[PDB]
Image (cartoon, coloured by chain):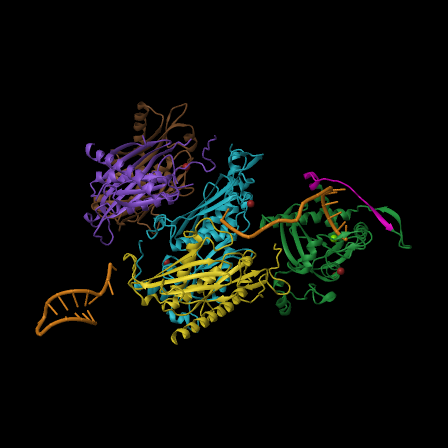
Chain colours: A purple, B brown, C cyan, D green, E yellow, F orange
Amino acid sequence: QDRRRLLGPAAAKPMAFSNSEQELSLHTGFIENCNGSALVEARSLGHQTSLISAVYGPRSIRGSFTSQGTISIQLKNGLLEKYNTNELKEVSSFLMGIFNSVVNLSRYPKSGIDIFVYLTYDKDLTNSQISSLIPHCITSITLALADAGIELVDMAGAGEANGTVVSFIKNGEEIVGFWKDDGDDEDLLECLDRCKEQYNRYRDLMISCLMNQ
Amino acid sequence: MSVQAEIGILDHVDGSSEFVSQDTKVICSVTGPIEPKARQELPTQLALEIIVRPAKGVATTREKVLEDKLRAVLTPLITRHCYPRQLCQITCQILESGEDEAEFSLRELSCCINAAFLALVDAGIALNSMCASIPIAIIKDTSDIIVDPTAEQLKISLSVHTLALEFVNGGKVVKNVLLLDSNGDFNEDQLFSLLELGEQKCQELVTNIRRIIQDNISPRLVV
Amino acid sequence: AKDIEISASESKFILEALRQNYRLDGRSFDQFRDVEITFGKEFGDVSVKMGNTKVHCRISCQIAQPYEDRPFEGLFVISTEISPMAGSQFENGNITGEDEVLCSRIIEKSVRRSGALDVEGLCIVAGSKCWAVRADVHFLDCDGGFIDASCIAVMAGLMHFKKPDITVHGEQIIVHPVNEREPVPLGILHIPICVTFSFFNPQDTEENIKGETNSEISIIDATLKEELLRDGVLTVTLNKNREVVQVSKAGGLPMDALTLMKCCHEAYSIIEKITDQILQLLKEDSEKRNKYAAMLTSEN
Amino acid sequence: ECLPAEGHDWKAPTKLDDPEAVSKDPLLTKRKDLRDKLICSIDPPGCVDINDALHAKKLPNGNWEVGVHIADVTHFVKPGTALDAEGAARGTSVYLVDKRIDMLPMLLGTDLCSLKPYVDRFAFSVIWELDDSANIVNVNFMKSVIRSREAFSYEQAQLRIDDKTQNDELTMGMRALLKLSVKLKQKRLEAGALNLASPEVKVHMDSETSDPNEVEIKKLLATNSLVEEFMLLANISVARKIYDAFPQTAM
Amino acid sequence: MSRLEIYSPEGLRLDGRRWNELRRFESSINTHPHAADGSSYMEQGNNKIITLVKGPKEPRLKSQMDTSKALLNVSVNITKFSKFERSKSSHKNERRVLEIQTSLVRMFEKNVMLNIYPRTVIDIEIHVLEQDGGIMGSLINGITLALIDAGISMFDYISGISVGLYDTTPLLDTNSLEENAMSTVTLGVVGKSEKLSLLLVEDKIPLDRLENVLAIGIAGAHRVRDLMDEELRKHAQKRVSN
RNA sequence: CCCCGAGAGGGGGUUUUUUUUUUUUUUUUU
Ligand SMILES: [Br-]
Ligand SMILES: [Br-]
Ligand SMILES: [Br-]
Ligand SMILES: [Br-]
Ligand SMILES: [Br-]
Ligand SMILES: [Mg+2]
């Protein structure tokens, strides 16, 4: 099959089988390989998620010259739940826009800050699901950047409510990103309030993690 | 140990050779020292580009391991500090496995080591010393140690071994053991009995190689 | 990549020699290099040599399942990966370069597409199990003519190769080893042979586009030096049945149509001699293996 | 319309190097000349469509030269034409006591291609060199031009062989054919050849009245075994040659 | 074995054309002024081709720069909706496409005066919107027109044409149905000459028929040159008169 | 060679894909 991997025999076919509000866990700086890293685990109802973020930078960019730094974000599929490459790219773009509003790029001329988020373990226990993972990604990237020592304007956090994801800064006064799939009609005000509550809780736990730990 | 080799068979390469042991035939080529790619450049030493091509099909991860082990042998052999920021391309084209490639890569690796060494000699690249490699195997019932085993012997083996030693002083002094690749079930007593008999047959091989090298190269030189 | 530096003196000399009916190797403009074919111990092992040009081909096969679209046809692939062994001009694994893709496509259209191999006879059980024949070409030493050398290497290999005999019990495939019963040869519908022409413009471009009398020089089977100084290439493939298998003049120096036709007729005389040559070397190889089989049984 | 423009007055060129003849037929240079050979055809009484023709000479090295000559139909029927189309469609000509539905037009099958006696005819010849024990030493295939000495009948040929009054070069060759026929038939049966039988009756229609009145039986003469053995020999050698040349599409 | 009348006894083809008639040939110059220095929209039969010439301009990488000539690049985009049956995979890295791109470059390297544009790059982007036989010949005509529109110097026109061989009957300008039923020959003729820039035969052709097929193609390609030249002078007069 | 300066100074000459009307005796000459 592939000349770079061992994928086994081709006639083989994969095994198909027959028939509080949120619980968080935060850890930072456990990857010596990079500059900043974070572990974010969430458990709620019939879905738990364990994702790992890793920040590599600021490192060299050998092309032209830039007064500010350049951020790149890449999401990788984990072991269990898989997602479309397109969908992972879309979230990556959405995350790039968010942290280009938070990261003090002016302090890193001709430098690159490459942020990796590994969707290691995403279990679906219900015996576009990507929308519920987005706030946890932002939490991991924020923790990793702060752990790396990359300057941030403010602790960026987010929340999710009925397929709507919105990330806040400045005590929830302003918005650094808005995401909406499916959901209902004229439910904007309700989503903003519910997400700001999650944003506030996540921000408190993040600060608590960056300080005490 | 009735191997047969030829030197300087390729025209558009700085050095080449063709080593044959039983059914295992490998042709090797060496170009260097030459201009290296930027990603290959080493500020002080020589950069080695080592390529192994299989007898059947295209190069896979299997040959990637053959390249890696062959690198462990050739690297300390070459006086690399003589060629800073420079490149030496080393290509091995295995022409005939001489073994079940689906199970073993023993004879192909040893033949590649011997051929690469010969190609380096032909190319006139600074070497710290000489080298010889032999394949060894241990049979099931008899548990005898067979040097240079056949393909049929490998099928009924309990362990397979690749031994490559570094020789100096006219091929009499074992400077070091460049590579020992032991795979399968074996005990400590078997290991040293292997190393003792292996060193003997290796020393015999160097002597034979020294003969081949002088027989081919001397007509080129002047008296 | 790594370039071959050609001085103005060398460029002017080789071209001027052509203007005086001289080529460095001493051949003629219409002269094809002597092709030497050596068979190994195993079937499908063939070594082709044209002057300094050295290529080696190895034919192999393994049990596989046919595509859904073609349940009656077996699998057949041709590999021609270049390596720095043929020269440092070639990048290791460069399978997208202009010359590489062309060569890869010429061979494919000459052997695969042309149906030189009977892929229908590669089927063991329809839509389930079949043979997967593989032709691996190894470019050892390059002195031009890699296409012509490969086409001969592949064809000589396919005609020399023999696959293990198979008896079928429903879907249970009984693969007889060479020790039990003898192996079975492959089915060859026709024998395609490539002949490559190299074109040289002794004058300038203006006299090629608007010049009255044509003066472009064409030589058969160019060496490396002649190959690096040509202005156009033509690869024509024929067989003893007096038919054109494929023709490929992918751009290059504009050439007169009648001259290209002349090349096709000149190539036909070469492919005839080459085909008969291959057949003879195959017979003698068969006679050699049988004579040893008789001397092995008599001593047994 | 695919038939020659000459018609029934078609003729093989006297010289095989004649400028006009070579201009029309550039393949004529490959045509061998066996008009010096003593060719004869052994076929039933009312046979006008002759396919085969035989001859035999004794080479100076003691061996025999046997030549089986078959009608060169290919020279007249070309692929793509309507003549070839109808020829393939019919597949074979049917044989009845009443009539005879030909596969090819009368002008072609019962005149031009037909290896008639006393005339120059194109033919595809197969020549063997074999010993007295009918063992093939070598075999050559070649398109040629011949001239049949005489078109014998099976009864007429047998009488000419047996009478021992006629010892001309032709009859001496005919006996040589029969002698080699016995050898070839012997070896073949020893090799495991079958000898089935179904000699159907021949309706002897009353040639004095109209309706059929008599039913007799056809007798197998030694000349029938003569022709049969050499026809088989021709088919075998050709089969080996065409399969060696076209291993995948050999008829 | 074809059950359709590829060439009826009345000398008529499946589309109505006779043996020596070109398809509907409609050229179009300066179609994308804001996207390229030169552009052409080709309609040869049901074939629809957009051709863009971008340059001569600065190379994006100084590593790839020639101080003696311009760098000529050609990328052919055969869209997934070019045929009746939509192709699932892309053709961008297909070996067949790489050969086509390479072929086109090797054709115009000896026609476009690259020597008078040193240290520059000429990028040729092609989009095949619809395909119906003789796509190679249409690709050639599209590049020639677009290059001229860009004001890039060249020695002469290069006209492309395809000729099929149904048994013994030559068929000028083949469509998809005819190409599936017979072997075809693609020609690339320079100007009004007999010189071929491109000779492409991918299927079996008798050696005796090849010369006659070439003769038909060259004659047909000359007509393509005239149509290209005609439409170009027409556009020239409409622009120079303002 | 080209640009610059009242005084032979300086700057440059570019880096795998449009392929499927299915039926009951050997051999030879007809
Ligand atoms: Br695997
Ligand atoms: Br099939
Ligand atoms: Br040379
Ligand atoms: Br009639
Ligand atoms: Br007569
Ligand atoms: Mg007869």
Of all residues, the one furthest to the right in this rendering is D209
Residue C123: x and y in percent read 55, 41
Of residues A38 and B42, which is closer to you in this image?
A38
D20 with respect to B205 (left or right) = right
Q: Nearer the viewer, residue C43 or B52?
A: B52
- Where residue A56 sits, quadrant-wise, is top left
> Residue A13, position in %: x, y?
46, 35
Q: Quadrant of residue E55?
A: bottom left
Q: Is residue C12 visible?
A: yes
Camera-side residue of A118 and D21: A118
Image location of residue E38, percent across then percent down: 37, 65
Expressed as whole percent of the image width and height from the top left, the position of residue B83 reads 22, 47
Q: Residue drawn 61% across and 55% down?
A: E2
Residue A30 seen: no
Residue B33 is inside the magenta segment: no
Q: Is residue A13 above or below residue D29?
A: above
Residue lying at the far bottom in this picture: please name it. E241
Q: Eyeballing the image, is B120 above or below D67?
A: above
Q: Determine whether D180 is above or below C225 in the image.
A: above
Instruction: Give the total number of marks visible in the rendering.
Output: 0
Rendered residue at 48%/55% (across/down)? E82
Q: Which residues are magenta?
A: D187-204
Residue C126 relative to residue B199: left or right: right
Closer to the camera, E7 or B188?
E7
The residue depicted at 62 percent of the width and 47 percent of the height is D240
